[PDB]
Structure formats: C-alpha cells, structure tokens
Image 1 (cartoon, rainbow, N blue to C red):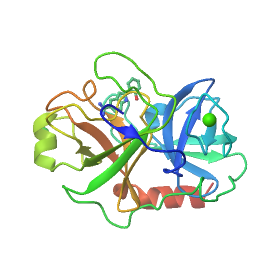
Image 2: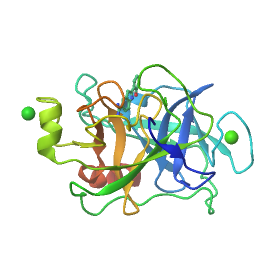
Image 3: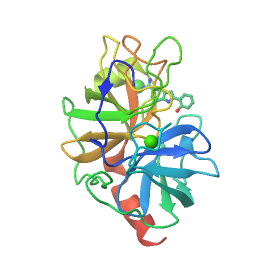
Length: 223
Ligand SMILES: NC(=[NH2+])c1ccc2[nH]c(-c3ccccc3O)cc2c1
Ligand SMILES: [Ca+2]
Ligand SMILES: [Cl-]
C-alpha cells in the first residue's frame, strides 16, 4: 500500500496473508473454511495465515492453516487478467472471534464515489521496494467507468473497476494482490493490477466481486 497508514493490530479481521515461506499475496476470509484471493496469486504449497498484524513476529491471535485446494476461475485469462478470482478451501475451519472474522459478499455492486478500505502488506514505495512488517490501510473511492477506461483504454472488462486517486501518491501495489476492497461492510473488490504503483492517472484495477457471487456460492456449495 503506497500512501496509506498502519491499520492497527487486528482492526481488519478478515484479512489473510498467503504464505509459501514468505508473504506473496493477501486474501479475504468469507466463512470459516474459505478465502477469496486473485487467480494470479495461485501456486501450490500455500499456507493461509489468519489473525496477523506483524507477519514476521508471532504476537498471538495467529492461526496458520494449510490450503486443502485452490480453485482458479475456469475462464481466468492470464494475459488480460479478466476473471482474476480464486477460492481457497482451508484444510480445517478457522476459529472465528473478534480478531479473525469473515467479511460479507455483496448483494449489489457499488457505485462510483463509494469510499472503500483496501489493506495489505505490499510494497509501500512507488519507486523502489519497501515491504512492511505490519498491515497497511488505504481509504480510496471507486472511480467512474469513463475515467477508468480513459486511463486504461481497451484493457478494462465489465469484471473490473478502478479505485484510487488520479493525482498519484496513494495506491495498492505488488504484495497487496488478492486482498480486499471493502465498502460499507461488503467485499466489493480484489486487488488485481495497475501500471506501476501510485502513478498519476494510472489508478489500481480491481476484480468486480458483485459479478461473481452466484459463482462463489455454487462453487462452495459443491466442494
Ligand atoms: N498499482 C496497483 N494498484 C497494483 C496492485 C496490485 C499489484 N500487484 C502487482 C504484482 C506485481 C508483480 C507480481 C505480482 C503482482 O500481483 C502489481 C500491482 C499493482
Ligand atoms: Ca505475526
Ligand atoms: Cl475502451
């Protein structure tokens, strides 16, 4: 997260860190046995870390659970990142409490101007790499589709939306991929891609979760 602030320990209880010996992507807990992340974060050997704040220190509240299976959306296109969503089923259910809690899926899509909270342990520099130990937060609005398509002509599909600041300075970045974009208590986006991080007129692009709720529900019901 570039230009964001320290969230404060466990203030984002649905945030998870996907780990394979180091933090490589974020994710969101939607129930006690399933996490939603981005399809481009897929790899084998994923350990899901819940209740984290400092990812390099065991401070208490952490629950480390192995992934039993990861389900990448069948129509995921790695060249356009269209349908960039993945579901991860946990080997055992997590113990939910006030520090580990799931986030609700939306019943309707959010409108331009909605203010959302984006969080993650991704790079904090737009020019260079500085990875934080604790979770960073950024409040950002969803932009209109015209401003999004004008920033990325020909690369925005109906399954994507832009959120951020066109003046630059505040954005999600590498390491934040797969993590949550929460607006009014509902998971509306997944950190997916962008051009550089926090560059002027190049806002972050996110997977539009309201278009996948029936798919997430049907897939969880059958696995
Ligand atoms: N500017 C943004 N809003 C943004 C968000 C997530 C990102 N993830 C990545 C990324 C870069 C290299 C490898 C994996 C990634 O997810 C870039 C990147 C940029
Ligand atoms: Ca920790
Ligand atoms: Cl276009």
